[PDB]
Image (spheres, coloured by chain):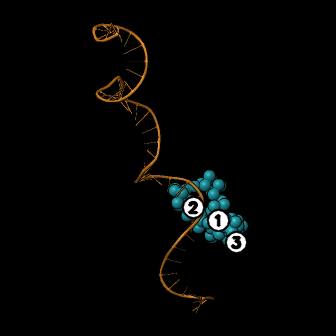
Chain colours: A cyan, B orange
Amino acid sequence: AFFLFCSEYRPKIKGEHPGLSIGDVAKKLGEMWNNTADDKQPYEKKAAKLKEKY
DNA sequence: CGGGTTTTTGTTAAGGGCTGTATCACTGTGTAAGACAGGCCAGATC
């Protein structure tokens, strides 16, 4: 949920207000994503689709 | 043999400072013997 959600919301969250380091940026953003599945499922669905396609 | 534990295993993803090889430009020189082949020739011989 949160992994695919961060890999999806990368553009705006990384080009609007990143933070101190890429580490802390993606950490806080993945936390917010996991605390949003209820609103991030299709990103994980696309991830699993690519995984099956591989 | 196996569902669910037993302690784990990728993995794979989003960017960033440190390390470890791979390049990059750039320079040191015309010899030294030996074998064989023609060409020239300067005395040998009839």
Residue beneath disc 1: A4
Quadrant (top left/top right/bottom left/bottom right) for the C terminus of chain A? bottom right
Residue A50: horizontal and vertical position, in percent? 68, 65
Q: Is residue A21 visible?
A: yes
Q: In front: mark 3 or mark 1?
A: 1
Circle 3 crowding by C-alpha within 10 Å: few under 14, some 14–19, many from 20: few
Which amino acid is tagged 2?
Answer: Ala
Residue A52: horizontal and vertical position, in percent? 68, 68
What whole-number distance in Å separates the C-alpha atoms at marks 3 and 1? 13 Å
Residue A28: horizontal and vertical position, in percent? 57, 64
Q: Looking at the image, which is closer to me, A3 or A15?
A: A3
Say whether residue B34 is left or right of residue A40: left
Residue that appears at 52% across and 56% down: A20
Q: Are marks 3 and 2 on the same chain?
A: yes
Residue that appears at 61% across and 66% down: A3
Residue that appears at 62% across and 70% down: A34
Q: Secondary structure at mark 2?
A: helix
Contact (Cβ within 8 Å) of mark 2 with mark 1: no
Residue that appears at 63% across and 57% down: A10
Residue beneath disc 2: A26
Which amino acid is tagged 1?
Answer: Leu
What whole-number distance in Å separates the C-alpha atoms at marks 3 and 2? 19 Å
**Quarter location, residue B2:** bottom right
Which labelled disc corresponds to residue A36?
Answer: none
Disc 3 chain ID: A
Dot 3 or dot 2, earlier in sequence: 2
Dot 2 or dot 1, earlier in sequence: 1
Q: Secondary structure at mark 3?
A: loop
Position above or below: A41 against B38 = below
Residue beneath disc 3: A38
Contact (Cβ within 8 Å) of mark 3 with mark 2: no
